[PDB]
Length: 453
Ligand SMILES: Nc1nc2c(ncn2[C@@H]2O[C@H](COP(=O)(O)OP(=O)(O)OP(=O)(O)O)[C@@H](O)[C@H]2O)c(=O)[nH]1
Ligand SMILES: [Mg+2]
Ligand code: NA
Image (cartoon, rainbow, N blue to C red; front, side, top):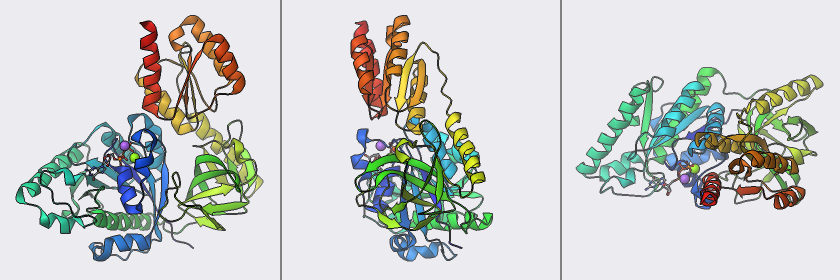
């Protein structure tokens, strides 16, 4: 019986510092390389317990109990308001969450939305009150524990931190939580612990990691979920074709044990795919599976929770955002297909049928672009995953007959088929493509405004 590696989801409002926090722990620069300077996908990173203990050093004694976890699997999530469905997926996967909140800006709309998600999935969480280094006159020392760094601050900075912390505590009370600075908490099951940190300079990461490990272990012990059992269950993050590996999928395995010869069922763009794994490859520890610096290593199995790449025949048509379910018998295959269909079908995007055509590369991207258009009262004709089809172009033309404004296709991280592009040129139907949600929408609006003039 192997010990579970817990999923730690990182949630919070746009720019409050989620990816910077993980980059400081990994010594990576994922945030610097994100297109459009925002997270737009779920990420997964293995942080071995040896790393936790090195960062924490003597502050591991902050937590009475011995930490027996093998490590932590951190799931990064988008803050941008459109990506509600990816924040929900991250919250639903988590054993414990880190709610990142800018101590200077305080609660904002996706802080509140994240809390509602954590309440919905009854996910325990710790709070990272980030960007303390912007308090006036703050004395920065890199990678210093908060309880050491706070001693370097003058009284004005200390008083400003406490004032801002009280604002956060009042906001948590508004939403039904008792919260305090982590070193003042008396009951870690009934109270929310707030760690003041600087993600960018590494202040307070030591105490934050000790609490994450301690509290996630406690959750798993309280639930009797610390031992991993059963066949593998996961969610697909990305579908890729890679030299020497073939068509692969990068996934999060959130329960059970995945083996390199397992039969699996995965969501597909047309229909469910039943295949047998031929290789598993695991990212290096501290490498973000969605933006890796290193090639992955072949492994025979992974135990939950883990990020892993799967090589198997027939994965070219796999659908990102859909389940991967190990299915060792025919009965299991039948069950897995229905569970996959339920997940796919449930993406419900209301369409006005005199509106825009929306295509995207993953289910999470399709939902985000759809949600953002609805918020902007841009009617949606149709929304589906995959490259722009000739049909998509013909449907857009029909809309164009009724209302040229909406006789358009928006393609989020997708390509245009050749016969679709031929027809679109001949019939003068516009197709917008992009890989940054806010820029794709701005491009569609700029085209609308400028055409009217
Ligand atoms: N001064 C300061 N800036 C920070 C800190 N943490 C993050 N930032 C900065 O805030 C900006 C946004 O940081 P990100 O890590 O992308 O924030 P995020 O929460 O992951 O953002 P989204 O994923 O798009 O919601 C960047 O310019 C970071 O350098 C911090 O501790 N101090
Ligand atoms: Mg981010
Ligand atoms: Na950002």
